[PDB]
Image (tube, coloured by chain):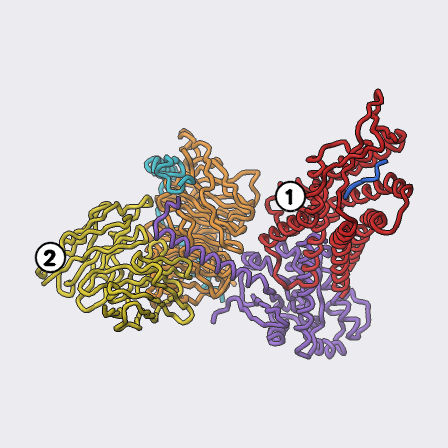
Chain colours: A orange, B purple, C cyan, D blue, E yellow, F red
Amino acid sequence: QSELDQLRQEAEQLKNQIRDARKACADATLSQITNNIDPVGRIQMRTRRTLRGHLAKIYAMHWGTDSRLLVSASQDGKLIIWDSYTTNKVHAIPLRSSWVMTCAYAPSGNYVACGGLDNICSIYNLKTREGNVRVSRELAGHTGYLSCCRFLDDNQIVTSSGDTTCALWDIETGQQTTTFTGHTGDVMSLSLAPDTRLFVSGACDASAKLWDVREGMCRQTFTGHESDINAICFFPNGNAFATGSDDATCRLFDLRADQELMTYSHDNIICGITSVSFSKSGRLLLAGYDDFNCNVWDALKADRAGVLAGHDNRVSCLGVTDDGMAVATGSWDSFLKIWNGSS
Amino acid sequence: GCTLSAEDKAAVERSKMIDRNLREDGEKAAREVKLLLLGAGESGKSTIVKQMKKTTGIVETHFTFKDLHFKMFDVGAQRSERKKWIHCFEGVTAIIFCVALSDYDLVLAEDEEMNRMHESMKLFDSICNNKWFTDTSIILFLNKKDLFEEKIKKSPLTICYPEYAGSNTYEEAAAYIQCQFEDLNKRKDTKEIYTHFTCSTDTKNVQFVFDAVTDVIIKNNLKDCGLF
Amino acid sequence: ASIAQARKLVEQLKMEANIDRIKVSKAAADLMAYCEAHAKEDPLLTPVPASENPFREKK
Amino acid sequence: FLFQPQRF
Amino acid sequence: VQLVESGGGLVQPGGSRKLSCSASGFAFSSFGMHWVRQAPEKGLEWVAYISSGSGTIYYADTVKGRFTISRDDPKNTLFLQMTSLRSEDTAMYYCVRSIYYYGSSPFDFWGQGTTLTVSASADIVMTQATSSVPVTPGESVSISCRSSKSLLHSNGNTYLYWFLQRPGQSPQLLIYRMSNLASGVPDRFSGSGSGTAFTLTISRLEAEDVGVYYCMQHLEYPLTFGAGTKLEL
Amino acid sequence: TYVNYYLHQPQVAAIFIISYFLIFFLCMMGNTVVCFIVMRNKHMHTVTNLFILNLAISDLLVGIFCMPITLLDNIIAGWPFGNTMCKISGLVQGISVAASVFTLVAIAVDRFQCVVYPFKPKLTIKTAFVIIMIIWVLAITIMSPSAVMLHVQEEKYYRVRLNSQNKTSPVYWCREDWPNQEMRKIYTTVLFANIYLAPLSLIVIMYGRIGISLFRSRKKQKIIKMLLIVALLFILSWLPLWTLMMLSDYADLSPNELQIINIYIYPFAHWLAFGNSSVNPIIYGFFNENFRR
């Protein structure tokens, strides 16, 4: 009706005003500022460890805060916790639902989480007197598949689902403390800020949104991608984040300027991006692709600084340790590989 | 030398035990048949599940038939982008696609065209010719045979298929729509469409599913062996 | 009948349009400064000697 | 002569 | 978690006896099991060890050949078949659970113990020079320990364990790997030492902490205990 | 008497050389293209691929160890080498032939399990390696008695006379010396049963079961046709060699007939057997569909 059309025009006016503001703050592109800096060399990471034992496609991995223990989920109904230094299997958690799509490691190391097509985020207790891993809680309430989950602390976890919503959970009570709505498509990934005061989510509507955890509101919406955003990761400084999408481009967005900074794409790359991750200093942007290899990007110059080609199937997982010593890649060939440099 | 501490050796032994258990679980899961259930909203999926047997997630049902324990996965409650999770069921033995024979006349909430049979055909086209299911056979199930027989006495098939020039009897109409469903396949060389008209009896649909799964497994074994 | 949805959308857009933004040059300088300050603390960017590498294959 | 082809 | 041992009592020298321990409240199959004996008015002495899954079995030199250790995982029972019993076998036998992975806490739970009575070179030496320390509540007391060889390994771990045996009670774990506090232990306990001399510090000592403190190494499987330092109130 | 080097006219001799050379090349090319794809492909290490690789190895060993030596024995009057080479050649030729036949049997077994018993667990790689080990060991010890006793005795009735200056040389024969003919008969019988009778019976039985279970499409007819072709090939190619062996072992053949058969049709039987060994990798690598990727 008339009111609906007036509201649509008003919203278009806000969109135009926001675009004009972003253009106004756009004076010099980040490529020009870093045009004088010394380019990084040829990054030549090589496989240091191969983690075998999964019998199906690995869908998610997450490093522990000690940079030694990592967890992986591989859709064979198993959650394996690895000792990356020795390739020993610390734990093997059987999942009630074998359709797991994400996994998380608590910063304290006492819990792991997983979820998938069952629309349930299951919390597992690792430090039990019985010596086995038990399901501490089964968080239900999402109407779609679970895409990502990240622990804030031992009692708070934020999940993203295919019902176009993100939720913050109180693990002890089991209820949704806050619901984050506004995405018009499936939310595929989320990344927590270093201070855990904010988090970004990338959805299938080719947009990324910044949420305030306590207030439960969307602060900024970032556009620019042409397809679904499958990956997202915060810059180590916390003032920027990078997104990986199905249009074969990785993009860097800065919160303060509220716009795109630089696009990481190549003509020879036409497959989508499954995972992104930043280096310890944020100089290197690692991204996993569907062409079975991971490309290392100079985050300040959009130059491919190296290739991590060691997987026979799609690279679905990516993770750099807290100390930045190693990077782990998960893949659909049921293998995890730990990569490191040499000097 | 070993150059390992006592605790390191014990941890290695624990990892070996975990590896053995994982191998046993994988061997157990290898001797299982995984079927993906697909269809329309009211395409007889519930009747199919009851014939071979918290949240609106994936519904997994098990049933053993002649020492061939099956796993049927129902994803009809996933109201999200199919392309974002359809690749999870890449290695399923077969896809059980259920359509209702009585939907040729019925029209869903979208009154303007969008015949339920046409909607199911469009769904069948997307799944049969999907990128992930290029070698996955489809066990097509045609449900509600009796309702189709009763509805065909008055309502002609021309409403759903104006190009149809056959008789109004049940046999020719059923064969024609089965041919329409089968011709949507664009990979006749790789995958095979098994078709069975669902009977009011209970013990015959599972027999057809078992037969089709046996044929699919034999063909897969032959392909792995290299005979064809 | 979607009027509440439109009101929510326009209110969210109004809240998004009221934030202050620094220049892109300033954000670029901040990112460059962070990358330069935390260099040579990056094992991936600057490889460490094999003695202090915990993932060395020699082990 | 050659009456010995031998086994195989 | 609960371990109950049975089968003790008076035995004739040269005879045989079958000790059994019943496990409850934890996954018995996932834990390695130890038998630790304690002669009357003496210190702890490791006897035997069976790995999880019975893959690995170790015996002390004084019991090798005569003692046999076995477990029945389905029924949650640990056995110790002792034959040719000597007068030196008179001791109280404990069953100790110990799980081994990265960051685990072995020797965390000890059974109540069953008493047995017989009516008649390369082993790391763990030295506790002090035997009895008079202590007063509210003060800080440090227990000293030493080892014949360095307990620090190339992987960075120092396999030294601290145990407390309250009077009329089974020993309990305080510190594992010389630095990590066992679960349920108050924060007032602390451990240190580099590779050969180790110290356990009890800051702001109170009651219920009196007893004998034992040091154990876990570097080589002929596990050795210290003589034990007694805290007398 | 006497005999001459270059036994007969150059026409039929060169025909023999050309034919045997043909088999060799065919065998070299087929086995090389079969083996190259296996090593270059890390993922192509399944049980059936391992068995095909073992068959290719056995066929290479059959070829390069049997066709040259057999050609020289049929082109040089007498046995022209020493005793150590005699024992080595006999052992390697027998082992290679037995390994090729038993690898064919194992391939038939693997195919039989995949069809009639589709729900049974697939054979593990360790099981495939164990089966290969049993195949090689059985090939070693089946005819070890024929290898321990070969001492290259010479004859004195005739002379090689070479081809230049009529240089007389002793004629050598590498025939085994059984202390009597009874164990000769029983050994040839068990070799026949264990190389032709039992393997062919097993292969035809499992292929018949495969066809029967398969009959319970357009491309399936290709499968049954290929199985029939393989079985008929294994019958026909190896039939004449064992037939001549059977006839020259038992019955009563006059010296003239024995001479004529040995110098005429026995090389033809060897040619057929080597053609079978050279065409085994051809069909098992070209008609094999997952190789055609």
In which quadrant will I find the N terminus of chain D?
A: top right
| Mark 2 Cα shell of 10 Å, populated few (<14), some (14-19), many (≥20) | some
Mark 1 falls within which chain? F
Which of these two is toward me, A222 or E181? E181
Separation of residues labelled 2 and 1 (CA atoms): 74 Å
In which quadrant will I find the C terminus of chain D?
A: top right
Answer yes or no: are tags 2 and 1 on the same subunit. no
* In this view, A246 is above or below E210: above
* In this view, E215 is above or below F58: below
Q: Which residue is mark 2?
A: E133
**Residue F78 placed where, x, y %?**
80, 33
- Label 2: element kind: strand
User: On residue F38, which mark appears?
Assistant: 1
| Total marks in image | 2
User: On residue A128, which mark appears?
Assistant: none
Where, by quadrant of the figure, is residue A165 drawn?
bottom left
| Mark 1 Cα shell of 10 Å, populated few (<14), some (14-19), many (≥20) | some
* In this view, B142 is above or below F5: below
**Residue E45 placed where, x, y %?**
25, 59
**Residue B116 placed where, x, y %?**
66, 68
- Left or right of residue E43: residue B209: right
- Residue F254 in view: yes
Look at 70% across and 40% down and name the residue there. F60
* In this view, A259 is above or below A301: below
Dot in front, 2 or 1: 2
> What's under tag 1, amino acid-wise?
Val
- Label 1: element kind: helix
Which of these two is toward me, A97 or E11? E11
**Residue A132 placed where, x, y %?**
38, 64
- Left or right of residue E155: residue F212: right
- Left or right of residue F193: residue B32: left
> What's under tag 2, amino acid-wise?
Val
